[PDB]
Image (cartoon, rainbow over all chains, first blue to last red):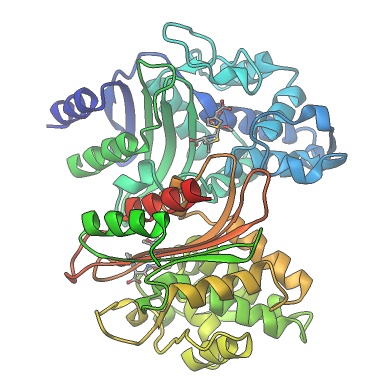
Length: 260
Length: 263
Ligand SMILES: *C(=O)[C@](NC(=O)[C@H](C(=O)O)c1ccsc1)(OC)[C@@H]1N[C@@H](C(=O)O)C(C)(C)S1
Ligand SMILES: *C(=O)[C@](NC(=O)[C@H](C(=O)O)c1ccsc1)(OC)[C@@H]1N[C@@H](C(=O)O)C(C)(C)S1
Protein backbone atom coordinates (compact mmCIF):
# COMPACT_ATOMS: atom_id res chain seq x y z
CA UNK A 1 0.00 0.00 0.00
CA UNK A 2 2.26 2.78 1.38
CA UNK A 3 5.16 2.24 -1.11
CA UNK A 4 2.81 2.43 -4.16
CA UNK A 5 1.22 5.64 -2.75
CA UNK A 6 4.55 7.41 -2.01
CA UNK A 7 5.92 6.41 -5.48
CA UNK A 8 2.69 7.81 -7.09
CA UNK A 9 3.00 11.09 -5.11
CA UNK A 10 6.66 11.45 -6.17
CA UNK A 11 5.81 10.78 -9.85
CA UNK A 12 2.99 13.40 -9.67
CA UNK A 13 5.35 15.94 -7.96
CA UNK A 14 8.04 15.72 -10.71
CA UNK A 15 10.72 15.83 -7.96
CA UNK A 16 12.70 13.55 -5.63
CA UNK A 17 10.94 12.57 -2.35
CA UNK A 18 12.64 11.19 0.78
CA UNK A 19 10.56 9.76 3.66
CA UNK A 20 11.56 8.12 6.95
CA UNK A 21 8.98 7.26 9.62
CA UNK A 22 9.77 5.68 12.99
CA UNK A 23 6.64 4.50 14.83
CA UNK A 24 7.85 4.26 18.48
CA UNK A 25 4.71 2.12 19.30
CA UNK A 26 6.53 -0.91 17.77
CA UNK A 27 9.77 0.49 16.21
CA UNK A 28 8.34 -0.08 12.68
CA UNK A 29 9.61 2.11 9.81
CA UNK A 30 8.31 3.48 6.45
CA UNK A 31 11.28 4.35 4.17
CA UNK A 32 11.24 5.93 0.70
CA UNK A 33 14.70 6.92 -0.65
CA UNK A 34 15.56 6.59 3.07
CA UNK A 35 19.32 6.21 2.32
CA UNK A 36 19.62 8.98 -0.33
CA UNK A 37 21.21 12.32 0.60
CA UNK A 38 19.04 15.46 0.49
CA UNK A 39 19.99 19.07 1.21
CA UNK A 40 18.82 19.75 4.79
CA UNK A 41 18.40 23.55 4.40
CA UNK A 42 16.85 24.99 7.64
CA UNK A 43 16.20 21.46 9.11
CA UNK A 44 19.95 21.53 9.99
CA UNK A 45 19.09 24.19 12.66
CA UNK A 46 17.79 21.34 14.90
CA UNK A 47 21.30 19.78 15.07
CA UNK A 48 22.93 23.21 15.73
CA UNK A 49 20.47 24.09 18.57
CA UNK A 50 20.76 20.54 20.03
CA UNK A 51 24.62 20.85 19.95
CA UNK A 52 24.42 24.13 21.99
CA UNK A 53 21.95 22.46 24.41
CA UNK A 54 24.49 19.61 24.89
CA UNK A 55 27.25 22.21 25.59
CA UNK A 56 24.92 23.82 28.23
CA UNK A 57 24.90 20.48 30.14
CA UNK A 58 28.50 21.25 31.31
CA UNK A 59 28.71 25.07 30.68
CA UNK A 60 25.79 25.65 33.04
CA UNK A 61 25.15 29.40 32.26
CA UNK A 62 25.94 29.10 28.52
CA UNK A 63 22.30 29.72 27.40
CA UNK A 64 22.39 33.09 29.32
CA UNK A 65 25.60 34.25 27.47
CA UNK A 66 25.06 37.50 25.50
CA UNK A 67 26.14 37.41 21.83
CA UNK A 68 26.76 40.64 19.87
CA UNK A 69 24.50 41.17 16.80
CA UNK A 70 26.31 43.57 14.40
CA UNK A 71 24.80 45.08 11.21
CA UNK A 72 27.43 43.12 9.18
CA UNK A 73 26.14 39.82 10.75
CA UNK A 74 22.66 40.11 9.18
CA UNK A 75 22.17 37.67 6.27
CA UNK A 76 19.08 36.99 4.10
CA UNK A 77 16.32 36.12 6.65
CA UNK A 78 16.61 37.77 10.07
CA UNK A 79 13.06 38.24 11.47
CA UNK A 80 14.32 38.21 15.11
CA UNK A 81 18.02 39.29 14.89
CA UNK A 82 17.20 42.51 12.92
CA UNK A 83 15.35 43.76 16.09
CA UNK A 84 18.57 43.35 18.19
CA UNK A 85 21.23 44.77 15.77
CA UNK A 86 23.85 46.87 17.68
CA UNK A 87 22.81 44.93 20.83
CA UNK A 88 22.97 41.36 22.12
CA UNK A 89 20.84 38.21 22.22
CA UNK A 90 21.46 35.26 24.57
CA UNK A 91 22.25 31.77 23.18
CA UNK A 92 18.75 30.67 24.44
CA UNK A 93 17.15 33.57 22.49
CA UNK A 94 19.27 32.67 19.39
CA UNK A 95 18.28 28.96 19.70
CA UNK A 96 14.56 29.89 19.95
CA UNK A 97 14.90 32.35 17.00
CA UNK A 98 16.71 29.73 14.85
CA UNK A 99 14.17 26.97 15.61
CA UNK A 100 10.80 28.77 15.88
CA UNK A 101 11.30 31.61 13.31
CA UNK A 102 14.11 30.00 11.21
CA UNK A 103 16.30 33.12 11.71
CA UNK A 104 19.50 32.63 9.59
CA UNK A 105 21.56 35.18 11.61
CA UNK A 106 20.60 33.22 14.76
CA UNK A 107 21.69 29.94 13.07
CA UNK A 108 25.07 31.53 12.17
CA UNK A 109 25.58 32.49 15.87
CA UNK A 110 24.84 28.84 16.90
CA UNK A 111 27.35 27.61 14.29
CA UNK A 112 29.98 30.14 15.49
CA UNK A 113 29.40 29.07 19.15
CA UNK A 114 30.23 25.47 18.06
CA UNK A 115 33.47 26.59 16.29
CA UNK A 116 32.03 26.44 12.75
CA UNK A 117 29.97 23.97 10.69
CA UNK A 118 32.43 21.18 11.63
CA UNK A 119 31.41 21.62 15.29
CA UNK A 120 27.78 20.80 14.35
CA UNK A 121 29.00 17.66 12.49
CA UNK A 122 31.16 16.74 15.55
CA UNK A 123 28.02 16.80 17.74
CA UNK A 124 26.19 14.56 15.20
CA UNK A 125 29.10 12.09 15.43
CA UNK A 126 29.07 12.31 19.26
CA UNK A 127 25.40 11.11 19.30
CA UNK A 128 26.02 8.28 16.80
CA UNK A 129 24.94 10.02 13.54
CA UNK A 130 27.67 9.07 11.00
CA UNK A 131 25.62 10.49 8.02
CA UNK A 132 24.81 14.15 8.85
CA UNK A 133 27.26 16.78 7.60
CA UNK A 134 27.21 20.57 7.92
CA UNK A 135 29.81 22.23 5.67
CA UNK A 136 28.68 25.86 5.26
CA UNK A 137 27.10 28.79 7.11
CA UNK A 138 23.88 30.59 6.19
CA UNK A 139 22.91 31.31 3.53
CA UNK A 140 25.20 29.18 1.28
CA UNK A 141 24.25 25.88 3.04
CA UNK A 142 20.93 26.05 1.04
CA UNK A 143 22.34 25.86 -2.57
CA UNK A 144 20.86 22.30 -2.78
CA UNK A 145 22.94 21.46 -5.92
CA UNK A 146 22.10 17.97 -7.28
CA UNK A 147 24.91 15.48 -6.43
CA UNK A 148 26.55 17.88 -3.90
CA UNK A 149 27.02 16.07 -0.55
CA UNK A 150 27.60 19.31 1.41
CA UNK A 151 24.96 20.13 4.06
CA UNK A 152 23.08 16.85 3.46
CA UNK A 153 21.79 13.88 5.40
CA UNK A 154 19.53 10.89 4.67
CA UNK A 155 15.92 10.61 5.84
CA UNK A 156 16.78 7.40 7.78
CA UNK A 157 19.73 9.08 9.61
CA UNK A 158 17.76 12.26 10.42
CA UNK A 159 14.66 10.37 11.70
CA UNK A 160 16.90 8.23 13.97
CA UNK A 161 18.78 11.32 15.27
CA UNK A 162 15.53 13.31 15.79
CA UNK A 163 14.19 10.33 17.82
CA UNK A 164 17.37 10.26 20.00
CA UNK A 165 17.24 14.07 20.51
CA UNK A 166 13.51 14.41 21.36
CA UNK A 167 12.42 10.98 22.78
CA UNK A 168 15.77 9.34 23.66
CA UNK A 169 18.90 10.24 25.67
CA UNK A 170 21.14 12.15 23.23
CA UNK A 171 20.49 15.16 25.53
CA UNK A 172 20.01 15.54 29.28
CA UNK A 173 16.40 15.49 30.59
CA UNK A 174 16.11 19.34 30.88
CA UNK A 175 17.72 19.88 27.45
CA UNK A 176 15.51 17.27 25.70
CA UNK A 177 12.42 18.92 27.22
CA UNK A 178 13.67 22.38 26.07
CA UNK A 179 14.24 21.14 22.47
CA UNK A 180 10.72 19.58 22.43
CA UNK A 181 9.20 22.84 23.83
CA UNK A 182 10.97 24.83 21.09
CA UNK A 183 9.86 22.46 18.26
CA UNK A 184 6.22 22.42 19.50
CA UNK A 185 6.29 26.27 19.35
CA UNK A 186 7.45 26.29 15.68
CA UNK A 187 5.70 29.06 13.66
CA UNK A 188 6.52 27.77 10.12
CA UNK A 189 5.01 24.23 10.02
CA UNK A 190 1.21 24.41 9.46
CA UNK A 191 1.44 23.82 5.62
CA UNK A 192 3.88 20.87 5.84
CA UNK A 193 3.75 17.52 7.75
CA UNK A 194 1.07 18.73 10.17
CA UNK A 195 -1.30 19.68 7.24
CA UNK A 196 -1.45 15.90 6.42
CA UNK A 197 -2.25 14.79 10.03
CA UNK A 198 -5.43 14.85 12.16
CA UNK A 199 -5.76 18.23 14.00
CA UNK A 200 -6.02 16.32 17.35
CA UNK A 201 -2.36 15.18 16.98
CA UNK A 202 0.41 17.28 18.62
CA UNK A 203 3.38 18.17 16.32
CA UNK A 204 6.79 19.69 16.93
CA UNK A 205 8.74 20.30 13.72
CA UNK A 206 11.38 22.22 11.80
CA UNK A 207 10.79 23.15 8.13
CA UNK A 208 13.23 24.28 5.47
CA UNK A 209 13.45 25.39 1.88
CA UNK A 210 16.21 26.24 -0.58
CA UNK A 211 17.19 26.31 -4.17
CA UNK A 212 15.99 23.52 -6.55
CA UNK A 213 12.54 23.99 -4.94
CA UNK A 214 13.87 22.12 -1.89
CA UNK A 215 11.00 21.70 0.61
CA UNK A 216 11.67 19.87 3.88
CA UNK A 217 10.09 19.10 7.26
CA UNK A 218 11.26 16.98 10.21
CA UNK A 219 8.70 16.28 12.93
CA UNK A 220 8.00 14.50 16.21
CA UNK A 221 4.27 13.64 16.38
CA UNK A 222 2.14 12.69 19.42
CA UNK A 223 -1.01 11.04 18.03
CA UNK A 224 -4.08 10.93 20.27
CA UNK A 225 -3.88 7.88 22.58
CA UNK A 226 -0.74 6.25 21.12
CA UNK A 227 3.04 6.40 21.17
CA UNK A 228 4.92 9.16 19.29
CA UNK A 229 6.07 9.04 15.65
CA UNK A 230 9.15 10.62 14.12
CA UNK A 231 8.74 11.67 10.48
CA UNK A 232 11.23 13.16 7.99
CA UNK A 233 9.92 14.37 4.61
CA UNK A 234 12.58 15.79 2.25
CA UNK A 235 11.81 16.98 -1.30
CA UNK A 236 13.90 18.56 -4.06
CA UNK A 237 13.28 19.32 -7.73
CA UNK A 238 15.16 19.39 -11.05
CA UNK A 239 15.00 23.19 -11.77
CA UNK A 240 17.24 25.56 -9.71
CA UNK A 241 14.33 28.11 -9.58
CA UNK A 242 11.53 25.57 -8.78
CA UNK A 243 8.62 26.69 -6.54
CA UNK A 244 8.24 25.30 -2.95
CA UNK A 245 5.90 22.26 -2.63
CA UNK A 246 4.84 22.08 1.06
CA UNK A 247 1.69 20.27 -0.26
CA UNK A 248 3.94 17.29 -1.25
CA UNK A 249 5.13 16.98 2.39
CA UNK A 250 1.50 17.24 3.65
CA UNK A 251 0.50 14.53 1.11
CA UNK A 252 3.40 12.25 2.25
CA UNK A 253 2.35 12.69 5.91
CA UNK A 254 -1.32 11.95 5.02
CA UNK A 255 -0.23 8.69 3.25
CA UNK A 256 1.88 7.70 6.36
CA UNK A 257 -1.06 8.48 8.75
CA UNK A 258 -3.56 6.44 6.62
CA UNK A 259 -1.21 3.43 6.51
CA UNK A 260 -1.02 2.84 10.31
CA UNK B 1 -16.67 50.77 -8.35
CA UNK B 2 -14.98 47.39 -8.80
CA UNK B 3 -11.13 47.53 -8.66
CA UNK B 4 -8.70 45.12 -10.44
CA UNK B 5 -8.09 43.51 -7.00
CA UNK B 6 -11.86 43.09 -6.31
CA UNK B 7 -12.30 41.45 -9.78
CA UNK B 8 -9.45 38.98 -9.03
CA UNK B 9 -10.98 38.16 -5.60
CA UNK B 10 -14.37 37.60 -7.34
CA UNK B 11 -12.70 35.11 -9.77
CA UNK B 12 -10.99 33.32 -6.86
CA UNK B 13 -14.34 33.16 -5.01
CA UNK B 14 -16.18 31.83 -8.12
CA UNK B 15 -13.61 28.95 -8.42
CA UNK B 16 -13.65 28.30 -4.61
CA UNK B 17 -17.20 26.91 -4.17
CA UNK B 18 -17.77 29.25 -1.21
CA UNK B 19 -18.12 32.83 0.04
CA UNK B 20 -14.97 34.95 0.56
CA UNK B 21 -14.64 38.09 2.71
CA UNK B 22 -11.51 40.29 2.60
CA UNK B 23 -10.51 43.53 4.29
CA UNK B 24 -7.08 45.16 3.86
CA UNK B 25 -5.90 48.29 5.65
CA UNK B 26 -2.62 49.65 4.26
CA UNK B 27 -1.25 51.88 7.09
CA UNK B 28 1.06 53.54 4.45
CA UNK B 29 -2.00 55.63 3.35
CA UNK B 30 -4.85 54.20 5.56
CA UNK B 31 -6.64 53.03 2.36
CA UNK B 32 -8.93 49.98 2.50
CA UNK B 33 -9.53 47.18 -0.02
CA UNK B 34 -12.82 45.35 0.77
CA UNK B 35 -14.47 42.27 -0.77
CA UNK B 36 -17.83 41.46 0.90
CA UNK B 37 -16.36 43.80 3.58
CA UNK B 38 -19.77 44.42 5.24
CA UNK B 39 -21.09 40.82 5.08
CA UNK B 40 -21.11 38.73 8.28
CA UNK B 41 -18.93 35.62 8.65
CA UNK B 42 -18.51 33.19 11.57
CA UNK B 43 -15.27 34.21 13.37
CA UNK B 44 -14.45 30.75 14.84
CA UNK B 45 -11.00 30.90 16.58
CA UNK B 46 -10.27 34.44 15.23
CA UNK B 47 -12.59 35.59 18.10
CA UNK B 48 -9.75 34.60 20.53
CA UNK B 49 -7.87 37.83 19.63
CA UNK B 50 -10.74 39.97 21.05
CA UNK B 51 -10.90 37.83 24.23
CA UNK B 52 -7.12 37.98 24.85
CA UNK B 53 -7.12 41.75 24.12
CA UNK B 54 -10.02 42.29 26.58
CA UNK B 55 -7.97 40.56 29.34
CA UNK B 56 -4.89 42.67 28.37
CA UNK B 57 -7.14 45.76 28.80
CA UNK B 58 -8.16 44.50 32.30
CA UNK B 59 -4.43 44.04 33.10
CA UNK B 60 -3.80 47.81 32.53
CA UNK B 61 -5.40 48.51 35.96
CA UNK B 62 -4.12 45.23 37.62
CA UNK B 63 -0.30 44.89 37.17
CA UNK B 64 -0.42 41.25 38.50
CA UNK B 65 -3.54 40.09 36.59
CA UNK B 66 -1.59 38.04 33.99
CA UNK B 67 0.03 36.11 36.92
CA UNK B 68 -3.40 35.26 38.45
CA UNK B 69 -3.93 31.46 38.60
CA UNK B 70 -7.05 29.82 37.09
CA UNK B 71 -8.08 26.27 38.11
CA UNK B 72 -8.25 23.75 35.22
CA UNK B 73 -10.64 20.88 36.08
CA UNK B 74 -11.20 17.64 34.13
CA UNK B 75 -14.79 18.93 33.46
CA UNK B 76 -13.33 22.09 31.80
CA UNK B 77 -11.66 20.24 28.89
CA UNK B 78 -13.57 20.69 25.61
CA UNK B 79 -12.68 19.53 22.07
CA UNK B 80 -9.16 20.99 21.45
CA UNK B 81 -7.00 21.49 24.58
CA UNK B 82 -3.36 20.76 23.68
CA UNK B 83 -2.05 23.05 26.49
CA UNK B 84 -4.86 22.98 29.11
CA UNK B 85 -4.99 19.12 29.22
CA UNK B 86 -1.41 19.17 30.67
CA UNK B 87 -2.61 21.35 33.61
CA UNK B 88 -5.86 19.53 34.61
CA UNK B 89 -6.20 19.44 38.45
CA UNK B 90 -3.71 22.34 38.51
CA UNK B 91 -3.66 26.00 37.45
CA UNK B 92 -2.66 28.20 34.53
CA UNK B 93 -2.10 31.96 34.80
CA UNK B 94 -4.10 34.35 32.60
CA UNK B 95 -0.82 34.96 30.64
CA UNK B 96 -0.49 31.18 30.07
CA UNK B 97 -4.17 30.97 29.02
CA UNK B 98 -3.80 33.99 26.66
CA UNK B 99 -0.65 32.47 25.05
CA UNK B 100 -2.34 29.02 24.77
CA UNK B 101 -5.53 30.51 23.24
CA UNK B 102 -3.64 32.66 20.70
CA UNK B 103 -0.58 30.59 19.74
CA UNK B 104 -2.07 27.03 19.99
CA UNK B 105 -5.80 27.92 19.68
CA UNK B 106 -6.58 26.03 22.94
CA UNK B 107 -10.40 26.06 23.37
CA UNK B 108 -10.29 25.43 27.16
CA UNK B 109 -7.97 28.45 27.44
CA UNK B 110 -10.43 30.59 25.40
CA UNK B 111 -13.27 29.51 27.76
CA UNK B 112 -11.20 30.72 30.77
CA UNK B 113 -10.61 34.11 29.05
CA UNK B 114 -14.37 34.36 28.32
CA UNK B 115 -15.19 33.52 31.99
CA UNK B 116 -12.64 36.16 33.21
CA UNK B 117 -14.62 38.72 31.08
CA UNK B 118 -17.98 37.61 32.59
CA UNK B 119 -19.14 35.50 29.61
CA UNK B 120 -19.38 35.98 25.84
CA UNK B 121 -21.13 39.38 26.30
CA UNK B 122 -18.06 40.63 28.22
CA UNK B 123 -16.03 40.10 25.04
CA UNK B 124 -18.68 41.99 23.00
CA UNK B 125 -18.66 44.81 25.62
CA UNK B 126 -14.88 45.20 25.14
CA UNK B 127 -15.36 45.32 21.34
CA UNK B 128 -17.93 48.17 21.81
CA UNK B 129 -15.51 50.00 24.19
CA UNK B 130 -12.85 50.11 21.40
CA UNK B 131 -15.31 51.30 18.71
CA UNK B 132 -16.30 47.93 17.14
CA UNK B 133 -20.12 48.03 16.79
CA UNK B 134 -20.15 44.86 14.60
CA UNK B 135 -18.37 42.07 16.53
CA UNK B 136 -20.59 39.80 18.63
CA UNK B 137 -19.64 36.83 20.80
CA UNK B 138 -22.74 34.90 21.89
CA UNK B 139 -21.42 31.44 22.93
CA UNK B 140 -18.45 29.67 24.51
CA UNK B 141 -16.19 27.00 22.97
CA UNK B 142 -16.93 24.84 21.16
CA UNK B 143 -20.49 25.84 20.12
CA UNK B 144 -19.35 29.31 18.92
CA UNK B 145 -17.95 27.47 15.79
CA UNK B 146 -21.25 26.02 14.41
CA UNK B 147 -20.85 28.63 11.58
CA UNK B 148 -24.44 28.10 10.30
CA UNK B 149 -25.16 30.21 7.19
CA UNK B 150 -27.36 33.24 8.06
CA UNK B 151 -26.78 32.80 11.84
CA UNK B 152 -25.64 36.13 13.38
CA UNK B 153 -24.18 34.47 16.51
CA UNK B 154 -20.38 34.74 16.89
CA UNK B 155 -19.96 36.77 13.67
CA UNK B 156 -18.28 39.93 12.48
CA UNK B 157 -17.56 41.62 9.13
CA UNK B 158 -14.12 41.76 7.47
CA UNK B 159 -14.19 45.61 7.61
CA UNK B 160 -14.93 45.67 11.38
CA UNK B 161 -12.33 43.01 12.27
CA UNK B 162 -9.57 44.68 10.17
CA UNK B 163 -10.26 48.04 11.88
CA UNK B 164 -10.27 46.38 15.34
CA UNK B 165 -7.08 44.38 14.68
CA UNK B 166 -5.37 47.62 13.50
CA UNK B 167 -6.45 49.55 16.65
CA UNK B 168 -5.32 46.65 18.94
CA UNK B 169 -1.91 45.94 17.33
CA UNK B 170 -0.79 49.25 15.71
CA UNK B 171 -3.07 51.89 17.35
CA UNK B 172 -3.90 52.91 20.93
CA UNK B 173 -6.83 50.60 21.90
CA UNK B 174 -4.41 49.00 24.44
CA UNK B 175 -1.57 50.45 26.55
CA UNK B 176 1.88 50.27 24.90
CA UNK B 177 3.03 47.29 27.09
CA UNK B 178 -0.18 45.38 26.29
CA UNK B 179 -0.06 46.22 22.51
CA UNK B 180 3.55 44.90 22.42
CA UNK B 181 2.47 41.71 24.29
CA UNK B 182 -0.42 41.08 21.83
CA UNK B 183 1.94 41.57 18.82
CA UNK B 184 4.53 39.21 20.44
CA UNK B 185 1.79 36.56 20.94
CA UNK B 186 0.44 36.87 17.36
CA UNK B 187 3.97 36.77 15.84
CA UNK B 188 4.51 33.45 17.73
CA UNK B 189 1.34 31.83 16.28
CA UNK B 190 1.93 28.14 15.38
CA UNK B 191 -1.11 27.59 13.10
CA UNK B 192 -0.70 30.24 10.32
CA UNK B 193 1.84 29.03 7.70
CA UNK B 194 -0.82 27.60 5.23
CA UNK B 195 -3.10 30.69 5.36
CA UNK B 196 -2.39 34.43 4.74
CA UNK B 197 1.40 33.76 5.31
CA UNK B 198 1.44 31.27 2.36
CA UNK B 199 0.35 34.02 -0.08
CA UNK B 200 2.96 36.66 0.94
CA UNK B 201 6.65 37.13 0.07
CA UNK B 202 8.89 35.17 2.52
CA UNK B 203 10.67 38.44 3.58
CA UNK B 204 7.38 39.89 5.04
CA UNK B 205 6.78 39.37 8.81
CA UNK B 206 3.33 38.11 9.94
CA UNK B 207 1.44 37.83 13.19
CA UNK B 208 -1.94 36.16 12.82
CA UNK B 209 -4.80 34.14 14.29
CA UNK B 210 -6.44 31.40 12.20
CA UNK B 211 -9.73 29.62 12.71
CA UNK B 212 -11.92 26.90 11.24
CA UNK B 213 -15.23 25.27 12.14
CA UNK B 214 -18.29 23.80 10.45
CA UNK B 215 -19.42 24.71 6.88
CA UNK B 216 -15.75 24.44 5.85
CA UNK B 217 -15.23 27.81 7.55
CA UNK B 218 -11.58 28.84 7.07
CA UNK B 219 -10.38 32.17 8.51
CA UNK B 220 -7.21 34.19 9.17
CA UNK B 221 -6.63 37.70 10.55
CA UNK B 222 -3.11 39.10 10.27
CA UNK B 223 -0.86 42.09 10.93
CA UNK B 224 1.85 42.15 8.23
CA UNK B 225 5.18 44.04 8.17
CA UNK B 226 6.19 44.24 4.46
CA UNK B 227 9.90 44.51 3.50
CA UNK B 228 10.43 48.31 3.20
CA UNK B 229 6.90 49.65 3.95
CA UNK B 230 4.36 50.46 6.62
CA UNK B 231 2.39 47.54 8.11
CA UNK B 232 -0.84 46.05 6.69
CA UNK B 233 -3.82 44.54 8.42
CA UNK B 234 -5.53 41.76 6.44
CA UNK B 235 -8.69 39.74 7.25
CA UNK B 236 -9.59 36.73 5.05
CA UNK B 237 -12.83 34.90 5.94
CA UNK B 238 -14.23 31.94 3.96
CA UNK B 239 -17.32 29.75 4.43
CA UNK B 240 -19.04 27.06 2.33
CA UNK B 241 -22.61 25.81 1.82
CA UNK B 242 -22.30 22.23 3.26
CA UNK B 243 -21.88 21.57 7.01
CA UNK B 244 -19.16 18.91 6.37
CA UNK B 245 -17.13 20.95 3.79
CA UNK B 246 -13.30 20.63 3.92
CA UNK B 247 -11.07 23.54 5.08
CA UNK B 248 -9.61 25.71 2.27
CA UNK B 249 -6.54 27.47 3.72
CA UNK B 250 -5.26 27.60 0.09
CA UNK B 251 -8.13 30.05 -0.72
CA UNK B 252 -6.92 32.41 2.06
CA UNK B 253 -3.35 32.11 0.72
CA UNK B 254 -4.67 32.93 -2.80
CA UNK B 255 -6.57 36.01 -1.47
CA UNK B 256 -3.40 37.22 0.34
CA UNK B 257 -1.35 36.75 -2.88
CA UNK B 258 -3.89 38.87 -4.89
CA UNK B 259 -3.73 41.58 -2.16
CA UNK B 260 0.13 41.52 -2.12
CA UNK B 261 0.32 41.67 -5.97
CA UNK B 262 -2.17 44.62 -5.98
CA UNK B 263 -0.12 46.90 -3.63
C1 LIG C 1 15.53 27.48 6.05
O1 LIG C 1 15.29 26.54 5.20
C2 LIG C 1 15.16 28.93 5.83
N1 LIG C 1 15.27 29.25 4.43
C3 LIG C 1 16.43 29.12 3.81
O2 LIG C 1 17.38 28.58 4.40
C4 LIG C 1 16.52 29.64 2.37
C5 LIG C 1 17.82 30.39 2.17
O3 LIG C 1 18.40 30.35 1.10
O4 LIG C 1 18.35 31.07 3.17
C6 LIG C 1 15.37 30.53 1.97
C7 LIG C 1 14.30 30.08 1.15
C8 LIG C 1 13.35 31.15 0.89
S1 LIG C 1 13.89 32.55 1.73
C9 LIG C 1 15.33 31.85 2.39
O5 LIG C 1 16.06 29.71 6.61
C10 LIG C 1 15.90 31.13 6.56
C11 LIG C 1 13.77 29.24 6.39
N2 LIG C 1 12.91 28.07 6.23
C12 LIG C 1 11.95 28.29 5.12
C13 LIG C 1 10.85 27.30 5.06
O6 LIG C 1 10.52 26.73 6.15
O7 LIG C 1 10.27 27.05 3.99
C14 LIG C 1 11.44 29.73 5.25
C15 LIG C 1 10.43 29.88 6.40
C16 LIG C 1 10.90 30.24 3.92
S2 LIG C 1 12.89 30.63 5.69
C1 LIG D 1 -10.52 27.71 16.11
O1 LIG D 1 -11.06 27.99 15.06
C2 LIG D 1 -10.07 26.31 16.51
N1 LIG D 1 -10.95 25.33 15.96
C3 LIG D 1 -12.23 25.38 16.16
O2 LIG D 1 -12.74 26.34 16.76
C4 LIG D 1 -13.07 24.20 15.68
C5 LIG D 1 -14.04 23.80 16.74
O3 LIG D 1 -15.11 23.37 16.40
O4 LIG D 1 -13.72 23.92 18.04
C6 LIG D 1 -12.26 23.01 15.24
C7 LIG D 1 -12.05 22.73 13.87
C8 LIG D 1 -11.26 21.57 13.71
S1 LIG D 1 -10.84 20.94 15.26
C9 LIG D 1 -11.69 22.14 16.16
O5 LIG D 1 -10.12 26.22 17.92
C10 LIG D 1 -9.68 25.02 18.57
C11 LIG D 1 -8.61 26.08 16.12
N2 LIG D 1 -8.32 26.76 14.87
C12 LIG D 1 -8.26 25.81 13.75
C13 LIG D 1 -7.63 26.40 12.52
O6 LIG D 1 -6.85 27.30 12.56
O7 LIG D 1 -7.93 25.84 11.36
C14 LIG D 1 -7.52 24.57 14.28
C15 LIG D 1 -6.03 24.81 14.38
C16 LIG D 1 -7.85 23.36 13.43
S2 LIG D 1 -8.14 24.37 15.92
